[PDB]
Length: 255
Length: 258
Ligand SMILES: N[C@@H](Cc1c(O)noc1-c1nnn(Cc2ccccc2)n1)C(=O)O
Ligand SMILES: N[C@@H](CCC(=O)O)C(=O)O
Image (tube, rainbow over all chains, first blue to last red; front, side):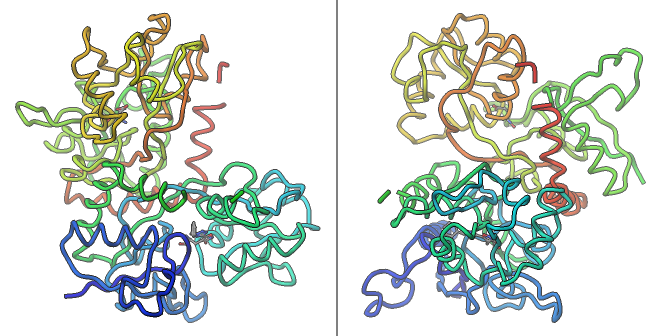
């Protein structure tokens, strides 16, 4: 009956509307993914329930318990029927779930507090005074972990052992750390967020250099899911009619 | 174990004739981005393959009259080719009849002009008629403008479909030659990938202006219900994550006559 949608609370994808306290159900939320979910549901003709992933994670497989967490986990163990959020299409995930073609293209990038003397990944790698890290249980950490590229390889050996920990549990925590570390902390995140934050007060962060790779976000469903193929056609249609660019301009519409 | 028939297309730097092709046989006649990818794909998946240039030299579209598919898409649809490894754009009409792996390259529609031409964006193009402009036939780009309800693009399509002489070209090479020979009176709408490649080729007289009109990607394609599909998709994502696809792009794109 009601499709259970798992998504994550990350502006401008999903955020609490003002005065949400007296609101109920899906009306409590607004954002890029909120509108996209509505679109998908409208064209596919089904009711749905937005639910914030319990642990607030994107999705990774515990190196020990070998159990998947985050939104990926919700789909794998059957808690959600579909994930509609900025979930990165990767090999280890495609091995356990299905993704539609990307509804957004992006790449890993570098966020620094304005004034920080670093222009690129090469810059970060050769020094240590300026610390840097990424999010836990995400596609960025994994990217560096599996990279054999000298540049990105060096960076990993540095992060994997840095103390105190350069890793963060949430993205909002990685941004907050840059803003508060007087230039001693650079953050590695996806271009999408780096751009969003650069146009926000106190307008003290910025993206430097080009992206380190080219990937995309896809709508995810349990492996061999029935809704899968239909959702993919729906998404390609929305993109081709220019609605997805419209949504992007709307939510990425200080500094 | 059977030799996999791979349909591809002659579009530099994806698939090009090697300098000594006249005295060479089969796959050794070609070189390029896609030739290298086909090799990488074939290696990991463990199978032998035969590169075959698509007979009509087209990408793929369904005929408005006969309703028959042509190009590489046609090769897959009618069972002539087992797989397509080329810069084939992932699109709705195609996904309806064939399968695509996830993108091995990202791009968007762009504007190529003869340097010095007074045009900076699609909006500029649509607001005048002194400078003609068109696109490639039987491809995703022409279909984009035909189905766009966006003011600018809609207006651009209204002009193009009725222009005289025709503003459409059969191959990308033809589009580039027209830009170069028309003294600035013709602008060509094509995918950023090809536009940036040409910008680095002699006589270095063309250039991309404005930003992409959309965002999409190229994907390896297989017939619907193909056992190769899923496996090749994972193989491509792997190559992508290891950076092999970016190194491959550098090689054939920037490793540059300008
Ligand atoms: N998407 C990654 C997570 C992930 C990761 O590993 N490193 O960085 C991110 C990331 N950064 N931003 N976003 C999403 C975003 C939020 C708000 C505005 C713009 C974009 N995700 C994953 O699926 O693991
Ligand atoms: N990539 C396009 C061809 C080039 C173009 O249409 O500009 C296709 O697959 O049809």
